[PDB]
Every structure is written in C-alpha cells, then in structure tokens.
C-alpha cells in the first residue's frame, strides 16, 4: 500500500492530463496565439507542488521543570485563494511529506465544494497522551506564535483547524494567543482559526458537519436514477442497507442521518472488533452503549462479527476511519455497490481500478468528507460578520410567514361570507416546529446541504463531459484542477 | 570526509560540553537554586537547532516563454539577536540540510566577532549559468517577495547577502524589489540586504573585507610569541612563506595583503591547476594575468605544479575555496605549520585531530572568514545612519588636527624669539596622505581591524582558560556558545 | 512634612510665576498682540498636570496555583517631548498621586539636563519580597503587555526604567516581552526600556552614572570663582573636605570620585550609624569593608559618631539617601558651605530659605542627581543605534593620535641632524592607559560630564538673570519651565 503522497500526486497527474487537452481547445481557442498555449500547461506544473513549507523547532518548559524542544510544520499548498485553510495534527507520526500531501488534498477539496481557501496542513511531532493539559496548551500557544511571526496563521493568511488529534480547546487557545499578541489590532483576530468553542466564537453545527456532509454526499447520488441504474438500485423492497467502518464521530453521525431516512444499518466495526445484525441496528442505542462503557463490543441485539465489516453484504459501505482500508486484495470481495469515502484516502488507486471493473460507485473523499470544511468556511465568515447567523432576521421572517398565510386565509374567506371560516393561518406541525426553534445551526445545515448538492451536480457534469464512468474521483480532481487553473490563468504568474 | 552538518553539529556539541560545567559553577553559583541549574543546559538544546526554515517553490517565465518552477530555502538558525544575517546561494547542489548547517555556523561566527546578528542562510536549487541575466533577476525578485511575505527578508528580521554564487547585482535587485513592494513604507528598506552596489547603498570597502579579515586573522596570531613558539616560528631569516588554495576573491586579497607585509607567496592553486616558484609570486602580476586571460594557468615567472598546493612546502597554508579540502587522508602530508581557513569548513574533524597531533595551528573558519560579516554589520548600520561613515566629521577632525599641530608650534616658538622659526605644523608625509584622502573605507577598515584583534585576544584567552592548545576552533565555538548562551539566559524562553 | 506631590506642585508654581513676567516682555514683546499674550500663560496651566494616567488590574497565577489580581499605574506627565521616560516602582505604598508627582518631576529634571523625554512614572502595588523570582517575572511581563496595548510602553512612546525597587532583570523581561509580542516588527523594540543588562542591550557605565553625575555637578560649581567667593572657598591650604550621608550606590561613587580628585572625605553615615575622622577615610577600604561584612559599622581607621553626619564640619555635605533629611530644624546647624543633593528632595523648602539666609549653596536634586537620567537617554539611543559607542572609531582615533605625535616628532627632529633624537611619539602614561583601554563607558562618561557642565552653566545663568542667589533649586525649576514652555509655545495646543 503506497503512501498518501504518491497517491494524491497520482490522482492529480491523472486529472491534470485529462484536463490539459480540453483546457486549451473548447475553453480558449478563439484567441489562440501560436498554440504555444499548450505550453501554458506550466500553470498545472505550478499548481502541483506546495508553494511554502515552514518547519520549526520551539521550546517549552514541561511541568516538571525540564526543557524540551518540539518540532512541527505547516505547509501551504496553494495561495490561488488568499486564506489558506487546513488543520493541525499532533502525533509522533507526522512528516513534512505527509502535511505536504494533505495540504495538497485540501486545495483541491475546497475547490470541489467551492470553498475559497488554499490547501494547507500542519503537524507537531508530539504525542498528546504524554503531555499534561497545561503542557499541551503551552505547546499550542508557542506554536501559534512562531506560526504567526512567519505568516502561517492569520485571519487573512492561513486559518488553521483541528484534526482528529486536536480539539476545540487547542483551537480556542490558538485563537486567543493570536488575538492577544500579533493580532492584537486585527478586528477579525478571532477568524485566525476555526473549529473553536461557541463561547470563543465557534459556529453552531460544527460537530454534525462532516457527518451530515457524508449523508448529503450519498443522498445526492442515490437519488439520481442514471447512476442508480448502472448499479441497479434506488429499490422498492429493500430500499437501502448500509455498513460503516469506524464508529468515530463522522461514522456515528453518518449512521444517524443515513438511518433517520430509511436505510438500515446492518454492520458497524471499530478498531477493536465488529457487530452484525441483518435486521438493523439503532444509532441512538449503539451510541449510548459506546458511551456508557468502553467500546461497541458486546452490544445486545447484535452478534459480534470477526474482522472488518468491509465485506459484510450491504448496499452502502462507508469507510469512516483509518487510511488505506480497501486495497487490491479485499477489493473484489466487497458486496457493496456504493462506497462512500467518509475519511481521507480509505481506498487505494489499485482498489479504484477494481471497483471500476465491477461497477462500483466510489464517492470520493475529496468530495464526500468535505462537509466539515464547508462549515469551517462559514465559521470563518461568522467571525468576520460578528453576528450569529439569523440574529436579525429570524423574527422578521417568522412574521413575514404568518402574514403570507394570513393573506391566503383572508383572501380565501372572501370567497365565502365568513370572517374566520377557513384557516390557512396554520403552519404544518413541522413548519411550526421549525420557526419556533429557528437557530444558527439551521441556516448552516442548509448552507451545507446546498453546497453538497451543487457540488455533486458539478462532479456529475464534469464526469459526463469527459466520459468518465463511475470514476467519480478523477472526475472530481479534474473539476478541481480546472477551477484552480481558471484562477491562475485569469491573471498570470509574476505577470499575474 | 563527513558533511558540513555533521561537522558543525560536532563542533557545537564539543564546545557545548566544555562549557556546561563552568557555565554553572563560577558563572552563576552564588544564587544557586536546587542545582537544577544543570538542568538549564536545555538552553543549549534550544540553541543547537535552527528554529525556523522556509522552503518554497515559485515560478518564473523563462525568456523563451516556457514556465518553470524553482525551488529554494532560507533557514534562520537563531533569533537570539534580532536581524538574522546570512547569504544566498544559487547552485544545483544546495540542500536544506546544508543551509541549515551554514546558518548554524553564522550564528556562532557572528558571536565570535561580536556582530549582533542571528545565523541564517538561503539556497536556490539553480545553476546561474543556465539562466540569462534577465531570468536570473526575475528569479531573485520573486524569491525576495515570497521570502518577504513570510518573514525571511526584512531590515529588522533577516538581512540576506551574497555568496560565491551570487553578486552585488542580485543583492541590488533584492533590495529594490523589497523597497518597492512590501517594504515601501520602511525608512530603512535598503537595509534589507547587504553586499550591494555603492550606488544602491553599499559600504566602501566591502570587497577587500573578507580578505583583509583573513589577513588580520593570521597576523594577530603570527605576532603572538606564545603560539609562534609552539610552532617554532616568527622567524628572522625566512620571515614567512605562504600558499593559498583558491584564487577567488578572498584568496586574491589574502595573497595581496599577506605579501604587502613581508610574506612570500610560493604557490597558488585554482580549480584548474596550480603554480609554484620558491622565489615568490607577485599579487598584482598574478592578478592581472588572471584577468587579461582566462585562468592563472600558463603564468610566466612560475612553473605549473600538478594537483593541489595543499602539500607545497610553506609556512602558512590558506584554503580559500571549496569545502572539505583537508581530510584524514592528505592531512599528515601538509608541510605548513599554520592553516588559515579562508573559507567555511575546508578541514574535516578528522583532519583537525591530525593537525593537532602534529602541532599545527588551524585558524577557524568561524573566526578567520568573519571579516565579511563584520563589515556587513557596518553596512547595515551605514544604512540605519543613512550616511557614509565620516561624511560629517572628516573635515572637522582634519581641522582639529591642524589646530593641534599649530599649538605645539606656537607653544614651541614661545621658547625662542621668532614667530615662524619652528614648524611642527607639518604632518608626516603619510599623515598628509591619510588626511587628504580620508574616506569611508578608512573607517570601515579600522573598524574591521579592531574587531579582528579584539576577537583574536578573546579566542586566545578562552583557549588558555580551558587549557586547550592550538585547538583554536573549539575555543572559538566555545567562546560563541558562551555569548549566545548569556543572551538567552539573561532573559529566559517563554518567560524570557 | 508635606507629600512629594504638594512639594513639586509648589516648586512648579513658584518657578511658574517667576517666569510668567519675563516670559512675555523681553522674550517676545517684539510682535506683541493685544497684550493678551499674558493670557497665553495658559500653556503653563497645561504644563502643570499630567496629561495621561493609566491604572490597571491584571491577574497572575502565583506558583502555588492560586489566582490574584495586581494593581498598578503609569502616568505620563508631558509629551512635549515624544518618548516619555521614567521608571517602574514595585511597592505596596505606591499611589497614583505619587507616580503623578514623580512623573511631573522627571519632565522638568530631563529639561534641566537637556534630555529629550517627557516625564513619566509607574507603580505596581506589590512587595517583591513576597513573590518568587518566577512570579515577579510573570507580573512584570503581563504588566508590559497591558502597558503596551494602551500606549504606555513603546520605544517612541514611553520608555520605562528601573527604580530602587526593581532591577535590570525585570527591565530585561520588559524589553523581551515587548520585543516578542506587540513590538515584534519594531526594529527598535529593545529601545522600549532602558536600564537593561549589557547582554540585553544595556549601556556600559550605567552604574557609575548617577554617582559621576553628583561629582561633576559639584565640580562645575566649585571651579566657578564667583560662587566660590560668595562662599569663600576654592582654598589653598585645606583644598576641599566633604561628608556624605548614605553609603548606597550614589554616595559611594560620589565619595570615590570626589576623593580621586583631592577632596578628603571626613565622615560617612548610613541607616545604621556613622563614622568620622578628620584625617580622611578611603573609598576603597570602606567600600570593601561594607562588602566583606554587613554595614560600615566598626570600621578601623575611623571612630563612630552618633546620629547623622549632616552636622559634621566639612566643606561639602552630600545627602545621598532618604527624603527630607535637612529640615528647618537642624538647617542652621550645618557647618557645610555647599550642599550637593545626591538624592531626590533631601532638603525641605523651609531649609532652603535658611541656607539662603546663611549663604549656603545648595545644588538641586533636579540637576545634581540627573546623571542617571542622562546616561539613560544614551542607553535609549544605543538601542536605537544598534552599535556600541566607539565600535568604529576607537582604532581610527588611536591611529590618528599616534600620527599626530609622530609628526610633532619628525618635525622637531628636522631642527637637529638625527632621525630618532627627539621622542614625542610617546604618550603620557595616563594617555597610554586611556588609549589602551578605550571603551564605551569612556564615551558615556564623557557625554555625561558635558551634559552636567552645560546644564550647570545654564542653571547659573538662569539664576543671575532672575537675580536669584543661592536658590539654585528654583533657578533650576525656572530654567526647566522655560524650556518646556518654549516647546509648547513654538507650536500651540490644538493648533499646536
Ligand atoms: N478553491 C477554489 N479554487 C478555485 N476556484 C474556486 C474555489 N472555490 C470557489 N471557486 C470559484 O470562485 C468563483 C466565484 O465565486 P461564486 O461562484 O460567485 O460564489 P460560490 O463560490 O459560493 O458559488 C466560483 O465560480 C467558483 O468556481
Ligand atoms: N551573537 C551574539 N550572541 C550573544 N551575545 C553577543 C553576540 N554578539 C555580541 N554579543 C554581546 O553583546 C554585548 C553588548 O554589546 P557591547 O559589548 O556594548 O557592544 P559590542 O558587541 O559591539 O562590543 C557584548 O558584551 C557582547 O558580548
Ligand atoms: N525636555 C525638554 N523640554 C524642552 N526643551 C528641551 C528639552 N530637552 C532639551 N530641550 C531643548 O532642545 C533644544 C534643541 O537641541 P540641541 O540643543 O541642539 O541638543 P542638546 O539638547 O543635546 O543640547 C535645546 O535648545 C534644548 O534646550
């Protein structure tokens, strides 16, 4: 199994090529100049590599009193879009080649979901389990400082974020260190980082954001007849049955929402075992179980499978966990017709081939798990707007709505001598519940959905237009390289 | 035959251990807290490693019209002293690790000649021969820009400089780019980088700098009985005889000054051959002959020697060129008693150990080729002062001098009738030729000398203290670790 | 005894009036407009009170893990002159009114010595002796932050300093915290505060400063026939004798320097007891004595003398010490002809009247103890300059000197047929010692003594203009009001 970097690289060179051709001819051959426009495919040669990587070595005083000098790095892939966005990862297993990779992935991912950020990612060679809360904070702060002092943390230059090794606490600090130091005078200092506590300016609905993203990623394709007939789906007996590998945030939620709308979870499988039950498995039962005690292992109304649900017979297989989990090997032996990448790179470029041979719809990481990002965009904005979404409008709207009903009602009662005979002025229970409890989350969620939909379509289209099949991935990376390109091209280089 | 980095790192660790002890006891034992002060040695763990290193990719459109991304990096070793100082190198061999290493050397080298800058170094993976004057420029400039936007160029942050691969022409572009871009509003924009054209704000006497440095460097030890006895030197008959390896800038000047003061140059080898002549060689002659034609090859009044001049018989051997020229191999076969490192790292750690074992004094890169830097500091200051050293005082002092003389003359004529009898009022020829041709260069040269001398003693003292002998190099690394440490200590780290 | 506030306020109001008149008629009645110029004495109404005063309550987390708020202030008296200057006091008994008063003094004191800074002062209601080194640091840093966020610390705004209750360790932190936060980009961030360690950018000669000041103050006057006659001094038998309350910093150096030049110390006190001996006491010997063990008490070659030495028959009494030590009480009983205020407000107002009636020449704190301040202003520049005074000239000068001698020589020789018969070329032993050991302190000391002089002369003149006598104080306060007024006057207010 190749390393994340070789993979992305590949992916990019793949979609690069594909593009090239088209990218010149029916996209800009009305003003052709010595067809030395083919030569402008240098742009893509620029777009490939990370423009800036900062590596650091900064001390901290451990509680005990002894000094230690921590290493870390943050890589900014592309600044085609001014604020670079990307998380920070605290783990002994970080490498400047990894962060370069993952930064690479972000730049493209964003483009996919039309989030105006450049890819970037950081990593600190540290194991959080070996440091005290106190120590951690010391580290993150001093990381924020150097990061800022050289241009790799600013609300206009590079807005970091958490990764499954870091949390809101850290972000919060990052935000606060910045705001009370370098960014003392920036009226948007709290925009420097996203994924922060609501108290510290976070945005409601961050949690469920990646999860819901998955959901809408699958949904949008499931509901297309054209793809759901090259598979033989969108049923009328079994409806839909899925499987999730990885009961960590994303998974959970993905199970929660996928189940809240028909589908029936039939397997779940963490980094400690599995579960199985071709009758179904409730989200709010398994959740609670996972919470009350240790793992999901030994859960009633379910029988313990051995290994990794990846093969379990179902319609929708969702890999919401570790890297490379679907390889050349097991690739053929997967009974699912739909693979939803609820995690970065959970399928190899060997596995792709395969799933492609045997009509398998692989819904990209590069798209499916970009729900978090999409909301992180919003968080940013929120910060810039200095107001919770809706704070001014929810009441106005609510009124506008009762008027618009009340008008119906009046006008209809004018076609019958009465003054209260008809009653349109009543919203549908669900509507009343919506308006009653209108909150930021809602707007977000919506904004989320709308992005995911409009992006799916984009993907589709840019798949049909290059006649790729179920090669949703390369369709995507292509779609992205086009975008990123367009920007670079409509300007220049040092003659931008 | 190690590598520049293992070397320096070794040199540090060496001097770091030699100091630890006496860095606690006798330097701060009359305040002692739990003797957990020996745990403060973590200041040295902090020093060791470059704190920041930026690595970038950046395009340029060659003159044919094709695009090409270029790769480079700048590493700032320390920030103990605010404006990091260090050169830029343009060569296809540059490696992060090399830069990191050189940077490392600059911090220490600066401490050695009390120059307030922190070690830095840059390198662009390019081969200037393959680019046109117009492309090179393009390249520098964009380099500057990115280097600026991320805090690696700035009159108060990092101040680059040339290297054997780069020249005042580039430095002048760096400057202007900077001035006219990010530094448009800085009243000291031109201080962003030294080693630039007089026209652009250079400092008279930049050229001869490094060379003169090397000359004094030697001189100051060659005039100290003590050392010159260990060797059996400061002779009556032969006086002194020396050879230089590398007729580049530094090697040329060295030979020029060393000669002007007695010393006979017997051999001089370049990259393309050598020259020999136990009668002597004249600098001007062998200078004009290296200018009128190509190389120094086929020079009259001098037979051609085969190979290096490193083994020629002579008193003073001076390596003014490539890296690791003196290794464990040829070490034992050198006839010279004094090796003056007129370049960085031209002697391996193994070679040192030999040289010591056979009583050979090796005047450390760290110190000897620190002339350049020394004069760069001045340049910097020259720019801050916004005036050419002496512009205001020259004439005033000249006057003050004739008024001195004039008084002696009146006061000596009032011990003898007359009113013009005795004439002291006349300056010695020399004097008159130094007053009449006063210039910035003279102030820079003197300031240079003073710093070499003062340092020299410093070294000498720190060698005798730690009973070293002719290990002038580890004295000096010690002397530097001990300066860099003080600063750090006299503040702290996060609580600095 | 009144409070420092109501005293200064008084001293101002006294000079203020004494100026008003003359500060119209012979200093501007050429242009005269309506004679409503008398109404422009509102400038002094402005000059009297402190423009701004920041109070603040910050927290720190005491080693033991608790949480406590600290209170502190910083009052900027005037800004007539850009960078406010003034120290930081750490003590439970600091009151806004006190700093305010003290700030007020600085702004005139500076004027006196021609030091371009406005008067400021800060206090922190804290007793060091109750905090650990660590805790102190936390406190002095937070302070620096909050002080910088609101414009009360800044190299061009307000440059703090140390005060009896603080040291260079703290000033070093204050500097560092600024330079690493808010002032990250200021290429003069270490000019934010003075008094700091050499290793942190301090100036050489800061600890002999206030002492050498005192000296020069007294020396300047003692060598002025005029005064020295109204007294009856500048003797031929008993040359000069002196006493010095207080043996602290300033007293000690005072004694040292005055001694070194002929005077004979004939009594030294201290907050324990006193000494005595009409044959003379050596500075070195007492100094060491003080050091070796506890306090000056029980010093050989001298007999204890109950009380204070303020009465002890001398020639020159020096009050280096505590406040209000010479009151209406003892004031007539004082054998001394000249009182040199080594500290702030030693004498009362009452006492002044008396010493005036009985022809005493009190040299005002406002001037006498301004030597510290003066240097200080150099330390500031030092930072702002980025080079140790003399670093480029020492050698150049050395040389020029020798050339000077050498010409005198040669010239003289050419009035006698021999090439080495006359030997001027040899400095005086002193001269050679000054040339050999040149250093920054020399330039600093010089500069101090030229400020002292020039300002003594100014005070005199200003006292013979307003026919004041041996009222040196007011004469000073006046000299200062004048200065500070002229700045204001030659601009305006809102239309300044
Ligand atoms: N990461 C990206 N890289 C390049 N282009 C992008 C990226 N994200 C968004 N874009 C482009 O920005 C353009 C202008 O924004 P617009 O379409 O008006 O708003 P929205 O991006 O929210 O749909 C869009 O045409 C979109 O294709
Ligand atoms: N690179 C350095 N690291 C640590 N200390 C240094 C360094 N360079 C100079 N110093 C120290 O800075 C101190 C303060 O400067 P000073 O001695 O007044 O001027 P100069 O350094 O030109 O002699 C000196 O005592 C010197 O030892
Ligand atoms: N604090 C002050 N307030 C008002 N005037 C001042 C102050 N300090 C200095 N001055 C004035 O500034 C003027 C201009 O400076 P100058 O005399 O050339 O240099 P220097 O002040 O070092 O003697 C002087 O005439 C001096 O009287």
Image: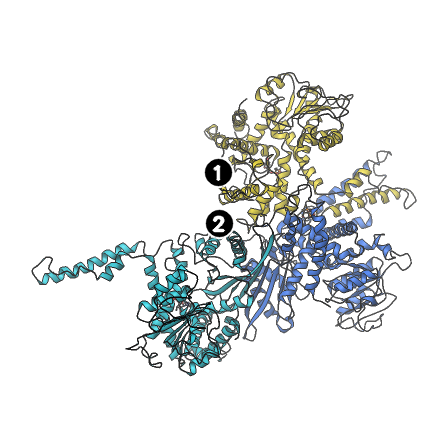
Chain colours: A cyan, B blue, C yellow
- Where is residue C421, by image quadrant? top right
> On the image, numbered disc 1 is attached to which residue?
C54
Q: Residue at x 73, y 67 (%)?
A: B322
Residue C275 shows in this picture: yes
Along the line of sight, the residue nearer the viewer: C148 or B175: C148
Mark 2 vs ligand 2: CB under 8 Å?
no
Q: Chain of mark 2?
A: A
Q: Is residue B255 above or below residue C455?
A: below
Q: Residue furthest bottom?
A: A357
Q: Is residue A78 above or below residue C190?
A: below
In the rendered image, residue A473, in percent from the top left (x then y), is placed at 43, 75
In the rendered image, residue B245, in percent from the top left (x then y), is placed at 78, 66
SS at mark 1 in the image: strand
In the rendered image, residue B25, in percent from the top left (x then y), is placed at 71, 46
Q: Is residue B243 above or below residue A173?
A: below
SS at mark 2 in the image: loop
Mark 1 vs ligand 3: CB under 8 Å?
no
Along the line of sight, the residue nearer the viewer: C103 or B423: C103
Horizontally, is C108 left or right of A451 in the view?
right
> On the image, numbered disc 2 is attached to which residue?
A180
Horizontally, is B279 left or right of B213 in the view?
right
Residue A32 shows in this picture: no
Q: Chain of mark 1?
A: C
- The lab-note entry on whether marks 2 and 1 share a chain reads no
- Where is residue B412, by image quadrant? top right
Along the line of sight, the residue nearer the viewer: C37 or C467: C467
- Quarter that holds the N terminus of chain B: bottom right
Pointers 2 and 1 in contact (C-beta within 8 Å): no
| Quadrant location, ligand no. 1 | bottom left
């Amino acid at each position: 199994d190749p390393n994340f970097f070789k993979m992305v690289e590949g992916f990019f060179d793949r979609g690069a090529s594909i593009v090239e051709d088209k990218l010149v001819e029916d996209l800009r051959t009305r003003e052709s100049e010595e067809q030395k426009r083919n030569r402008v495919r240098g742009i893509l040669r620029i777009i490939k590599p990370c423009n800036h990587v900062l590596s650091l070595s900064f001390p901290i005083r451990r509680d005990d009193g002894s000094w230690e000098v921590i290493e870390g790095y943050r890589a900014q892939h592309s600044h085609q879009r001014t604020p670079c966005k990307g998380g920070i990862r605290y783990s002994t297993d970080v490498s400047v080649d990894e962060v370069k990779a993952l930064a690479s992935l972000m730049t493209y991912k964003c483009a996919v979901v039309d989030v105006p950020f450049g890819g970037a990612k950081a990593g600190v060679k540290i194991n959080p389990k070996n440091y005290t809360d106190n120590e951690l904070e010391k580290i993150t702060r001093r990381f924020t400082m150097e990061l800022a002092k050289k241009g790799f943390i600013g609300p206009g230059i590079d807005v970091p974020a958490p990764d499954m090794s870091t949390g809101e606490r850290e972000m919060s600090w990052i935000a606060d260190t910045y705001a009370s130091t370098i960014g003392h005078y920036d009226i948007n200092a709290h925009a420097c980082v996203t994924g922060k506590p609501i108290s510290q300016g976070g945005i409601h609905g961050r949690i469920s954001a990646t999860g819901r993203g998955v959901f809408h990623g699958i949904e949008n394709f499931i509901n297309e007849a054209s793809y759901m007939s090259i598979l033989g789906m969108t049923p009328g007996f079994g409806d839909k049955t899925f499987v999730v590998q990885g009961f960590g945030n994303v998974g959970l939620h993905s199970m929660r929402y996928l189940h809240r709308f028909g589908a029936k979870c039939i397997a779940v499988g963490e980094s400690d075992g599995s579960i199985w039950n071709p009758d179904g498995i409730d989200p709010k039962e398994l959740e609670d179980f996972k919470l009350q005690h240790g793992s999901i292992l030994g859960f009633p109304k379910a029988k313990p499978y051995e290994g990794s649900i990846l093969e379990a017979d179902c319609d929708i297989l969702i890999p919401a966990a570790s890297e490379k989990q679907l390889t050349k090997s097991n690739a053929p032996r997967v009974k699912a017709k739909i693979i939803a990448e609820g995690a970065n790179g959970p399928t190899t470029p060997e596995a792709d081939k395969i799933f492609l041979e045997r009509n398998i719809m692989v819904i990209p990481d590069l798209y499916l798990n970009a729900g978090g990002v999409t909301v992180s965009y919003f968080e940013w904005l929120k910060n810039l707007n200095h107001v919770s979404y809706g704070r001014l409008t929810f009441k106005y709207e609510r009124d506008s709505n009762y008027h618009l009903l009340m008008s119906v009602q009046e006008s209809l009662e004018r076609k019958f001598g009465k003054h209260g005979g008809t009653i349109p002025i009543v919203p549908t229970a669900e509507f009343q519940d919506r308006i009653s409890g209108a909150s930021e989350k809602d707007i977000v969620h919506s904004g989320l959905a709308y992005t995911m939909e409009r992006s799916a379509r984009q993907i589709m289209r840019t798949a049909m237009k290059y006649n790729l099949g179920l090669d949703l991935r390369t369709a995507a990376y292509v779609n992205a390289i086009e975008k990123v390109f367009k920007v670079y091209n409509e300007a220049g280089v040092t003659f931008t």
